[PDB]
Image: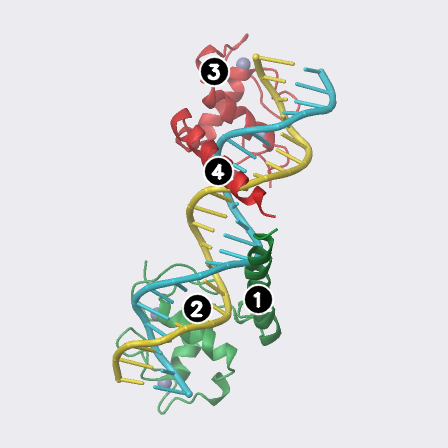
Chain colours: A green, B red, C yellow, D cyan
Amino acid sequence: ELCVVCGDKATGYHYRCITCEGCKGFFRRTIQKSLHPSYSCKYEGKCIIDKVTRNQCQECRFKKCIYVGMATDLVLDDSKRLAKRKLIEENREKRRREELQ
Amino acid sequence: ELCVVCGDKATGYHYRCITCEGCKGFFRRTIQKSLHPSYSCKYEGKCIIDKVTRNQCQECRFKKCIYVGMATDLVLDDSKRLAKRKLIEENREKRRREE
DNA sequence: ATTGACCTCAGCTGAGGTCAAT
DNA sequence: ATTGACCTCAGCTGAGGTCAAT
Ligand SMILES: [Zn+2]
Ligand SMILES: [Zn+2]
Ligand SMILES: [Zn+2]
Ligand SMILES: [Zn+2]
């Protein structure tokens, strides 16, 4: 119903939590690109994260992500990521060429 | 873990309950073919239904199924059941040619 | 005819990607 | 660069079917 991180309309389970597309995208790219160590809260690390303020502070938005339990292990590392892309191309290959003899 | 109907190894959800393949299949065909009205307990409708005695009393087995919550509506009626059949046949011939 | 271990498969769920807007 | 609404698609789930055994 409602994103556990920011509280706007959730789109289902993402990395083991009910979240909006926004918080899902954010968390995914934070882990994919390894951005969190470089996040920094300009004030007390206790920023309110709701849907109006969720872009006001990356550090606090990510911390709230980790807190509600989003699973960093469910974001594929780059090798697995590339394999998936390859597999998707091998299957758009297997289907593409198996459809012709 | 364990079938809520008869108590042996469950294979996950079926018609909204944790059940074995046996109780799944039993409940499926009872509904598909509409058999339950014809099931009759030869003793008090209180037969123990566990994994050894489950084939001893169909009526008691089925009543258990309804009690634990198995969903009759999740069993396709002939209308949509042959509708699923037709859908699968088309796909098998399309994918069979190719190759 | 009935049982149930084992199978196929449609459609869902939840991954990663895209790209107009910022 | 970043965000997020919307996308494609592998693989899971849970229906129905099969068939050796009874
Ligand atoms: Zn959110
Ligand atoms: Zn902050
Ligand atoms: Zn059972
Ligand atoms: Zn009985």
> CA gap, disc 1 to disc 3?
48 Å
Q: Amino acid at mark 1?
A: Lys
Please tell me in which quarter of the rendered image ligand 3 is found.
top right
Q: Do discs 2 and 1 belong to a common subunit?
A: yes
> Residue type at mark 3?
Leu
Q: Which residue is mark 3?
A: B35
Tell me: residue B19, above or below residue A21: above
Image marks 4 and 3: residues in contact by CB distance under 8 Å: no
Q: Nearer the viewer, mark 4 or mark 3?
A: 4
* Subunit bearing disc 4: B
Question: What chain is tagged by disc 3?
Answer: B
Which residue is depicted at the point 47% across and 19% down? Answer: B33
Name the foreground residue: A84 vs A75: A84
Please determine if labels 1 and 3 lie on a single subunit: no
Q: Amino acid at mark 2?
A: Val
> How much space separates mark 4 and mark 3, taking CA atoms?
31 Å
Q: Are marks 2 and 1 in contact (CB under 8 Å)?
A: no
Residue position for label 1 = A84
Q: Nearer the viewer, mark 2 or mark 1?
A: 1
Separation of residues labelled 2 and 1 (CA atoms)? 28 Å
Judged by depth in the image, the label closer to the viewer, 1 or 3, is: 1
Mark 1 sits near ligand 1, with its Cβ under 8 Å away: no
Mark 4 and mark 2 on one chain? no
Residue for point 54% across, 39% down: B92
The crowding category of the residue bearing disc 4, from other C-alpha atoms within 10 Å (few below 14, some 14 to 19, many at least 20), is few
* Labels 4 and 3 share a subunit: yes
Name the residue carrying label 4: B90
Q: Which residue matches tag 2?
A: A68
Output the chain of dot 1.
A
SS label for mark 3? loop
| Viewer can see residue B46 | no
Mark toward the start of the polypeptide (4 vs 3):
3
